[PDB]
Image (tube, rainbow, N blue to C red; front, side):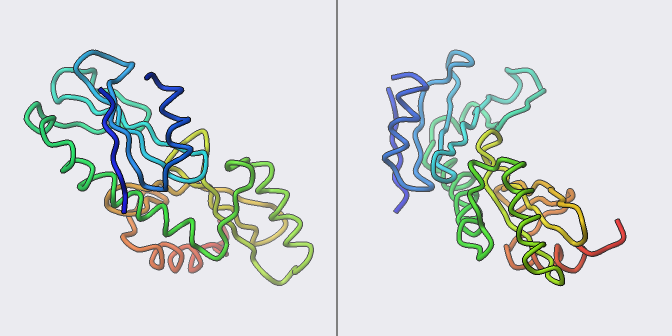
Length: 190
């Protein structure tokens, strides 16, 4: 039930190892970015791995773009707790999206594939508002939420975070609340 492997191999072998593992499994390994820092890689979905740069407070540049986790020097000693505290909830929220009735792979979250699917589905049932959710392979941890209220497909991002789903900047702690809000607003005049 969610295994963790600690490496004492470089990035590429880590992704090949994760191919064999289950969703939410974790590999903690030395970081390519810098000495004495770590990378916590976890399997978001099939072929999609988030590489969390674990940074020490006060010792790296305050700017980050990719998945990033700031911890103090002491917290580096209990990696298990950091996994339980931050990664495990995100893996669970990701699974909530993977099990959603309208989850679709769309070739790793290809926006064009999702738009084509939306247009096709809208032409099949004009009075229905189709929507699908897809994991972004190039932004691990982010999902595309595509939907077509009228004549044009629309795509927004949903971000998995340890405290729930971020959508339009708001945090939703349950998948059901996320989609209830979404469906209450997806026909708005925009």
